[PDB]
Image (cartoon, rainbow, N blue to C red):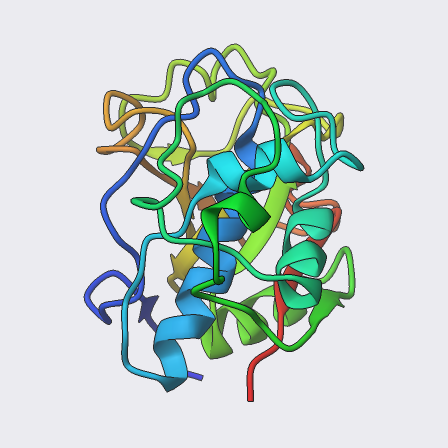
């Protein structure tokens, strides 16, 4: 369980993206999750469509609300297309999955990490990236243009992102905003403080598919 875990230089995460004026970080967080695992075994890095997840997942409320843990489940159940055969537009619409044709990616299950346990988060993040939530409605996290976020912030979780590494002290997160935020679309939050919930409630509820 290395002292350092970066999947970027591991060839697991692709360039950064923006959800835009679409409340859809859940579907984006997911595509990165599935994505990671998909490349971890096969040795093939891919960019899947979040747009599809939006238009297809009726359980989620597309362009403004969702469950990073429906998306995944969805995929495993059905599947998911490339981000070319289903590029992101930013507006929820009619499911094209079927109309689009044969799927391209399809997992083999979804599991959740025991909330409120850093030790647990890491491990999984060590075996493969994960979808995690937190407080973004933040007025500080909103302004982050590089650094190690400690706060201030709260325990009112309401935005989903992704963890793509950690250090002895900083946890790495991929944001669904442009590369005109944090440190090039990236933000480092601090771990090991005692805060069980985890600063910004980053330890509330996390997840991930399964792959054979």
**Going 76% across and 34% down the picture, which residue do you hit?**
58
**Going 24% across and 71% down the picture, which residue do you hit?**
10
**Can you give x and y, in whole percent of width and height, for residue 15 in the image?**
23, 45
| Quarter of the rendering containing residue 179 | top left
Q: Is residue 199 visible?
A: no
Q: Is residue 80 left or right of residue 178?
A: right
Q: How many marks?
A: 0
- Which quadrant would the N terminus be assigned to in this image? bottom left
Classify 156 as above or below 47.
above
Classify 179 as above or below 117.
above
**Can you give x and y, in whole percent of width and height, for residue 153 in the image?**
61, 23
Q: Is residue 83 left or right of residue 114?
A: left
Residue placed farthest to the bottom in the image? 212
| Quarter of the rendering containing residue 95 | top right
**Can you give x and y, in whole percent of width and height, for residue 156 in the image?**
75, 25
Q: Is residue 122 visible?
A: yes
Which of the two residues, 190 or 57, is positioned nearer the viewer here? 57
Q: Is residue 19 left or right of residue 181?
A: right
Which of the two residues, 89 or 134, is positioned nearer the viewer here? 89
Classify 78 as above or below 151.
below
Q: Is residue 90 left or right of residue 116?
A: left
**Going 74% across and 33% down the picture, which residue do you hit?**
60
- Which quadrant would the C terminus be assigned to in this image? bottom right
| Quarter of the rendering containing residue 116 | bottom right
Classify 93 as above or below 171.
above
């Amino acid at each position: 369980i290395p002292e350092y875990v970066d999947w970027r230089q591991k060839g697991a995460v692709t360039p950064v993206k923006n959800q835009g004026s679409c409340g859809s970080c859940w579907a984006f967080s997911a595509v990165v999750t599935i994505e990671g695992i998909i490349k971890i075994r096969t040795g093939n890095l891919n960019q899947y469509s979040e747009q599809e997840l939006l238009d297809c997942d009726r359980r989620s409320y597309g362009c403004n609300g969702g469950y990073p843990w429906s998306a995944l489940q969805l995929v495993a159940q059905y599947g998911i297309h490339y981000r070319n055969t289903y590029p992101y537009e930013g507006v929820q619409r009619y499911c094209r999955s079927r109309e689009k044709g044969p799927y391209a990616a399809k997992t083999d299950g979804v599991r959740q990490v025991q909330p409120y346990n850093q030790g647990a988060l890491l491990y999984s993040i060590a075996n493969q990236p994960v979808s995690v939530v937190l407080q973004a409605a933040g007025k500080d996290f909103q302004l982050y243009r590089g650094g190690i976020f400690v706060g201030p912030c709260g325990n009112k979780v309401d935005h989903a992102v992704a963890a793509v590494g950690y250090g002895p002290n900083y946890i790495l997160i991929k944001n669904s905003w442009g590369t005109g935020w944090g440190e090039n679309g990236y933000i480092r939050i601090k771990r090991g403080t005692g805060n069980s919930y985890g600063v910004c409630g980053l330890y509330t509820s996390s997840f991930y598919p399964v792959k054979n």
